[PDB]
Image (tube, rainbow, N blue to C red):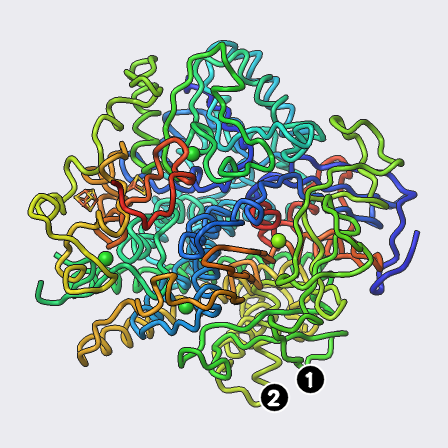
């Protein structure tokens, strides 16, 4: 047992293993210890995969890098490509034209919406929604709930819900439950009434059909989704209004139509569902899962209104420590003393493992070895030994501090910035105050529940808060790319049709040595790619990815990362059913392929 | 009685799962609810840990020799297989176990078919395609990074309708989707034939949609349905959106030189 960051770790209680953690991208093992009352007193995050992209990239052409690193992840598809072209452009002093900037922003915001909405419905919802309970729902009462939760959503009739319910009934009655097989249905950890379960499952099916439409924006500008194409120096989707070309006004009109559909979905389906589910779980008292969000949050800051001008970031970033929302520290990805990665408890080796390496000096040499207190063997692990190396995920820290990253972090940072006079953060602030009023007062009043008085400071550092922030961010991203589209069309019509700067396409024009960094506010948090170029080739290429931050194992000082902290202090209804573990872990939207790369 | 599908994940990026759920004809919703029984799939399944593991034995027993094994990703042979750990054991053990009683095996995408990005030089995990590990079962390769959504669901639809594996070429790919090179029906082919090429990004030629051969397009040596079926309900494909084909459906495409280096 030991104390760290206000958490009292104790591994003397009952040990529980969850492997595989499902409804995530990639591979994770989670172990916890619970006390005599089934409260989690220890949590262990193990990334159970590695591919070695950083090693594979060595000696290759920086212009090809984006395609390799894009394949780090097909869920957050393209965000690694964006980071990569930004890193190379930074190294080579390439400024991309305005249309390429706007097209990249639109692609980034499209990914945000798609990733967030699919995550909530298809990965997260079953932690909050009991599908078997939806079968018992009354269609008329479901209709009435729908109209209170979201008046503007036109799919609300009692007959529509009856049809959906009947299809689910027949599906379950077959004895082939498919993705619902061996679920935790009926657990007391589920609190929604049948009608809310039916409404949510209906929206699950709605979202499954609609999500394929949103990505057609990627298809227009990048040829395909998943894995749209990017380009060092700009975008490949050349523009010609009067021509035959990749982009004309009809293609841009198509993009606009998809954006408008996105805005309706976020406003009418996604945000209201999360507010309603959040309210009901708040009413049940399930405010667990805050972890590091209550103290330390970080993002690099993203979406500048004016290209290459960070002061205009619409999701302004920085770092907060010790829960002090009155002081945002600037974060510099170039500073060797800020972002550093330890491997003390990871399956890698450094020359000196007592220190953290800035990614320009990063090292990735695998070292799969288990501690002496492991139960089992090297190829058949029963209980992992977290006193030694226990994960394929490195341990990123900021000036030695363990930080939570993600939409929640960005929304806390936005709120902090807006309080200190930053007008670029006005919209996220408005969203948060609106959400708090809905969760505390308006939704309870509508559903006949008592009103509460939680402040944002109390409400946001929680699994509910983390889930809320993701939905709000999706909404905000949809709104922003709507404006980006207008700016793009305006620029084109003003006579600027440029999509690529090719001045430094040829390696003969490059400095013989160079380094660069590209950052992105990816769906799951702070993403950075750091590159060293030598004689036209990749000398070093290091990625520090949002789930690397969140899912990290312990550092040299024994400090815990966001996943492990979030599970602490959480009661379990049944220690053999990982409902609460999944609910909180999923609120981070873990991408394990990303985390390990 | 819907055919059970046990969808395993090895080393992968999950782009193949994502592509599958983009299908418009048929809708993935309809595939899952009305066509197959998707009984194991990490991305979507309710159960985790021990409860998830228990599904495998149950389906394998009840539907012995009558379930489809779908594999996304691949097994690593280095690190004693523990660069991909499932249930505290190497993924390769899960793969071999589930494969033994499968009616058919689908290798989704370039990862399962050939190795894909993790198998590119120097392949630190010794990531290995499914057919080099499972050597005693019929395997259909559905390559691409990822494959087209309708190609993936098209394979499933054929298999469910006929209870047979579609006709395969010598590399194990379904002829119904991989018989044509991108270059055969590419809409830029008239430009290629007229010697009309892009030389630099966003030159006048690029703005008129000229052929991308000199920008590295690998369409002439790449077999896929991208020029005809196209992507995301026929919205576009790489070449239409202005980037050359990078050869993503072909074995070892990551190690055939820069994507921007032209074919000779
Ligand atoms: S763009 Fe590529 S596939 Fe199309 S005609 Fe040219 S070389 Fe062939
Ligand atoms: S890159 Fe791949 S998606 Fe088609 S156009 Fe070439 S095979
Ligand atoms: Cl950019
Ligand atoms: Cl390959
Ligand atoms: Cl082009
Ligand atoms: Mg890394």
Where's residue B131, x and y in %?
47, 19
- Asked whether the beta carbons under mark 2 and mark 1 sit within 8 Å of each other, the answer is yes
Q: A256 above or below B187?
A: below
Location of residue A222 (image quadrant)? bottom left
Whether residue B176 sits left or right of residue B1 in the image: it is: left
Which structural element holds mark 2?
Answer: loop
The residue depicted at 42 percent of the width and 40 percent of the height is B254
Tell me the distance, in whole angstroms, between the alpha carbons under discs 2 and 1.
7 Å
The crowd level at tag 2 (other Cα within 10 Å; few <14, some 14-19, many 20+) is: few
Where's residue A434, x and y in %?
52, 75
Whether residue A438 sits left or right of residue A4 in the image: it is: left
Q: Chain of mark 1?
A: A
**Residue A152 in sight:** no
Residue, disc 2: A420
Q: Nearer the viewer, residue B26 or B114?
A: B114
Q: A486 above or below A58?
A: below
Where's residue A411, x and y in %?
57, 71
Which structural element holds mark 1?
Answer: loop
Whether residue B64 sits left or right of residue A329 in the image: it is: left
The residue depicted at 38 percent of the width and 37 percent of the height is B253
**Residue B254 in sight:** yes
Q: Which mark is residue A326?
A: 1
Q: A257 above or below B91?
A: below
Where's residue A328, x and y in %?
66, 81
């Amino acid at each position: 047992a030991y104390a760290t960051q206000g958490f009292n770790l104790d591994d003397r209680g009952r040990r529980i293993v969850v492997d595989p953690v499902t409804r995530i991208e990639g591979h994770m093992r989670c172990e916890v210890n619970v006390d005599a009352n089934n409260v989690i007193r220890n949590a262990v995050s193990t990334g159970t995969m590695w591919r070695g992209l950083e090693v594979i990239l060595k000696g290759r052409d920086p212009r090809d890098a984006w395609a390799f690193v894009e394949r780090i992840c097909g869920v957050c598809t393209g965000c690694h490509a964006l980071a990569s072209v930004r890193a190379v452009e930074n190294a080579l002093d390439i400024r991309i034209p305005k249309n390429a900037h706007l097209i990249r922003e639109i692609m980034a915001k499209t990914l945000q919406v798609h990733d967030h909405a699919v995550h909530f419905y298809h990965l997260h919802a079953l932690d909050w929604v009991d599908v078997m309970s939806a079968l018992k729902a009354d269609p008329k009462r479901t209709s009435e709930l729908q109209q209170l939760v979201s008046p503007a959503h036109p799919l609300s009739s009692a007959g529509y819900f009856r049809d959906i319910q009947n299809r689910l009934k027949r599906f379950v009655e077959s004895g082939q439950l498919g993705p619902f097989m061996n679920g935790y249905w009926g657990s007391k950890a589920y609190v929604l009434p049948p009608e809310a379960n039916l409404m949510a499952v209906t929206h699950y099916l709605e979202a499954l059909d609609l999500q394929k439409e949103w990505v057609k924006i990627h298809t227009i500008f990048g040829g395909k989704n998943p894995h749209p194409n990017y380009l060092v120096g700009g975008v490949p989707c050349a523009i010609n209004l009067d021509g035959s070309a990749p982009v004309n006004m009809e293609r841009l009109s198509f993009v606009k139509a998809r954006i408008d559909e996105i805005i309706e979905f976020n406003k009418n389906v996604y945000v209201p569902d999360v507010l309603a589910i959040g309210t009901l779980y708040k009413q049940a008292g399930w405010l667990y899962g805050g972890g590091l969000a209550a103290t330390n949050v970080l993002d690099y800051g993203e979406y500048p209104n004016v290209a290459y001008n960070k002061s205009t970031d619409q999701l302004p970033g920085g770092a907060i420590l010790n829960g002090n929302w009155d002081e945002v520290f600037p974060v510099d990805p170039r500073d060797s003393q800020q972002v550093q990665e330890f491997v003390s408890h990871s399956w890698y080796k450094y020359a000196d493992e007592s220190v953290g390496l800035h990614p320009w000096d990063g090292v990735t040499e695998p070292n799969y070895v288990l501690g002496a207190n492991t139960k089992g063997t090297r190829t058949r692990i029963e209980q992992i030994d977290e006193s030694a190396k226990y994960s394929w995920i490195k341990s990123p820290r900021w000036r030695g501090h363990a930080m939570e990253v993600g939409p929640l972090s960005r929304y806390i940072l936005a709120y902090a910035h807006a309080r200190s006079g930053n007008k670029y953060a006005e919209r996220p602030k408005e969203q948060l105050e609106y959400s708090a009023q809905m969760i505390n007062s308006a939704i309870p009043k509508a559903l006949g529940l008592p009103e509460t008085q939680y402040t944002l400071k109390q409400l946001l550092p929680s699994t509910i808060g983390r889930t809320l922030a993701r939905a709000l961010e999706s909404q905000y991203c949809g709104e922003m790319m709507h404006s980006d589209w207008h700016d793009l069309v305006a620029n084109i019509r003003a006579g600027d049709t440029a999509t690529a700067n090719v001045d430094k396409w040829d390696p003969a024009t490059w400095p013989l040595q160079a380094k660069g960094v590209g950052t992105v506010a990816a769906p799951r948090g702070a993403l950075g790619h750091w590159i060293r170029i030598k004689d036209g080739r990749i000398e070093n290429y290091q990625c520090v990815v949002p789930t690397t931050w969140n899912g990290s194992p312990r550092d040299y000082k024994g400090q815990i990362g966001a996943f492990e902290a979030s599970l602490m202090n959480t009661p379990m209804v049944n220690p053999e059913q990982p409902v609460e573990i999944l609910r909180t872990l999923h609120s981070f939207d873990p991408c394990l392929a990303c985390s390990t790369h | 009685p819907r055919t059970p599908v046990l969808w395993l994940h090895g080393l992968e990026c999950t782009g193949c799962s994502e592509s599958f759920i983009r299908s418009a004809h048929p809708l993935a919703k309809d595939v899952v609810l009305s066509m197959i029984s998707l009984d194991y799939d990490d991305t979507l399944m309710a159960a985790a840990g021990h409860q998830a593991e228990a599904i495998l034995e149950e389906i394998m027993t009840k539907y012995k020799g009558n379930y489809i094994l779908a594999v996304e990703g691949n097994p690593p042979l280095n690190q004693d297989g523990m660069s991909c750990i499932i249930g505290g054991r190497p993924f390769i053990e899960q793969l071999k176990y589930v494969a033994k009683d499968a009616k058919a095996i689908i290798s989704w995408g370039s990862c399962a078919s050939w190795g894909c990005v993790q198998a590119a030089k120097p392949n630190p995990t010794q990531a290995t395609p499914v057919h080099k590990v499972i050597t005693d079962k019929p395997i259909i390769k559905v390559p691409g990074c990822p494959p087209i959504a309708e190609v993936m669901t098209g394979v499933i639809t054929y298999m469910l309708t006929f209870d047979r594996i579609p006709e395969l070429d010598r590399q194990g790919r379904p002829k119904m989707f991989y018989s044509q090179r991108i270059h055969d029906k590419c809409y830029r082919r008239p430009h290629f034939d007229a010697g009309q090429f892009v030389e630099e990004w966003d030159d006048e030629s690029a703005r008129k949609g000229f052929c991308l051969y000199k920008m590295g397009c690998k369409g002439p040596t790449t077999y896929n349905a991208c020029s005809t079926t196209r992507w995301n309900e026929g919205t576009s494909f790489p070449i239409q959106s202005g980037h050359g084909c990078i050869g993503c459906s072909e074995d070892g495409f990551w190690d055939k030189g820069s994507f921007y280096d032209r074919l000779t």
